[PDB]
Figure 1 (spheres, rainbow, N blue to C red):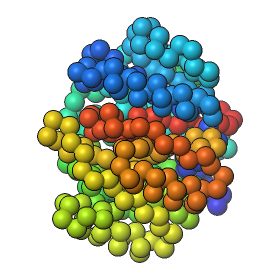
Figure 2 (cartoon, rainbow, N blue to C red):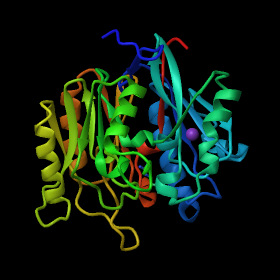
Figure 3 (cartoon, rainbow, N blue to C red):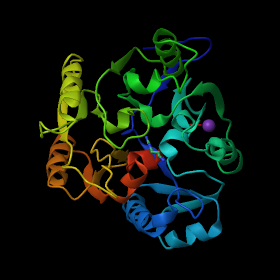
Figure 4 (tube, rainbow, N blue to C red):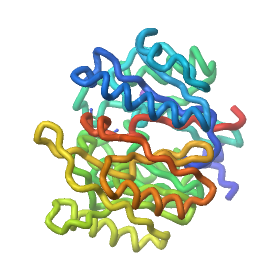
Length: 333
Ligand SMILES: N=C(N)NCCCCN
Ligand SMILES: [K+]
């Protein structure tokens, strides 16, 4: 579809497209990771080692000493920059194809409705693209997190109404204004707006990357709850019914049985996985459903190695694997 609008033809890139880097922001002394900084860093080591076997990894941290934990890992690069937190999925630049070339977008990030400090995270993209990539960066005057949106690459996007229409985000516009703006920015034909569904512990106002994800052009993998007494049951059932009306094939990702840290339910979701070259890295929570979701996804993705990575520690700060990384795609810049 050769559509041009105000000088540009735009294509949205799905996660399974070929990538150059996976980018992460390390936990450090002055982040909210402090009370268990070593447990989370041990988990990062595993995550990084697994990804590095398939494609390059870029680690962003505010001190040289933060990199010394990862020094002897193949295909790992380092970049010095100050950070508030580690959730680069939400503040990291987002690639699109603009007139046949890769171009990165730099949306404004306010930490999910100014729930935490966000001034340093906001400036990571400017500095990274100025010092490392030495590459122009498109400023977009619009509050958006990458975790709140999901693409199939044929011009269809997936998102949640509760997040994007929240008064703590872009309150000054309405649904029609927002739906229009995002279609122009990513050159989309369609946006699917999910009214129902959440994961308990999620402090991001119902990010789509905890609920439903495209795994190929035709297939959406989405969360459900097998336990009818769990608060997740009918919210995810209603969400499942919305998803049936889209016409896409569906793959079910049953949530684990409740996990707690300091008498607080953790937001475990198998939807927070990440595509890299030739592999899909999936979060494992040491529930019996780890095996079940791994077999399902693996059978549905015969060109990928599906790899489980222990993601329990990530949940203490209310995100998982996908939340903790950002994809930078391979192509002409
Ligand atoms: N990546 C997300 N969607 N959320 C991360 C939780 C942020 C709370 N410190
Ligand atoms: K930004």
